[PDB]
Amino acid sequence: ALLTPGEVAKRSGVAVSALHFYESKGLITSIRNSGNQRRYKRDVLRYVAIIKIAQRIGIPLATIGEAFGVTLSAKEWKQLSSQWREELDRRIHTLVALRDELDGCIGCGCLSRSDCPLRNP
Amino acid sequence: ALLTPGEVAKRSGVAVSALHFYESKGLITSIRNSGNQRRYKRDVLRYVAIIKIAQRIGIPLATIGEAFGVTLSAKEWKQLSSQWREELDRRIHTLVALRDELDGCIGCGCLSRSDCPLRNP
DNA sequence: GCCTCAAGTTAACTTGAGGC
DNA sequence: GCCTCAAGTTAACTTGAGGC
Ligand code: FES
Ligand code: FES
Image (cartoon, rainbow over all chains, first blue to last red):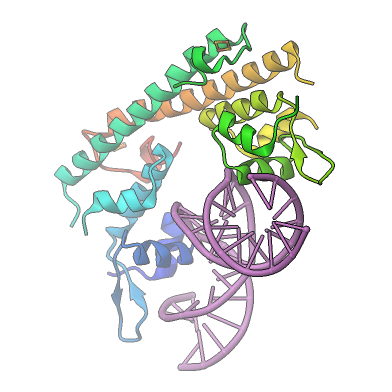
């Protein structure tokens, strides 16, 4: 059967307004019933779930749509997951570089413009 | 001598509007000259520099003020730097946990609510 | 409850109008 | 150039008004 906006909201843990928004930003799809009311394809649950994991990764909605294209496969998941495991990685290396630079500069405090890592990344 | 808003903007690499804002959010201080124009205590350069390093760490302005109290020592720097090297750390561990959880779920794609890490953090 | 659409919210600022 | 203050900008939504 098709899910009503309300249901999807409970099983997703997102506001119905959140679903309206995601659809307007084209991250989920709808179908209108005999009374213009939206009805969702179970699949939506998986997407929303993915939207949230993507958010945790620190990925912006626009980009999450930019990855969604415009019906969810096994390949797709592998395409996304990896594409994110990568950023999650780059991002981490970036933060780690900092932590190293930072540890050196703790006994310093000079913050030399032309000579300190922390300042000239 | 005292620095003019313009100078401080060039040596900081921030908009004069940025300096106005930081001061209003109480992260830097000013002194008005005979014509109500602001004049800065060189020290401001170090703060701004710190505001930016704090931002890189991923710290919010409010919090950066929350750490600044309301005249910059050696102890202060150690108080801040550490206090940030810590968050920079917690944050990293969080991202790393994800990356691990994520790697397991790549050959899966089940996204079992009551059974997958990625979903129930 | 569900639908629409306008406007408000936080963050970190920027842009613009008005005036010296 | 610098000063003030009101309003605009992006992001991710939420709140509210109005109507079925
Ligand atoms: S604190 Fe001196 S080089 Fe970074
Ligand atoms: S992808 Fe199946 S448990 Fe996470």
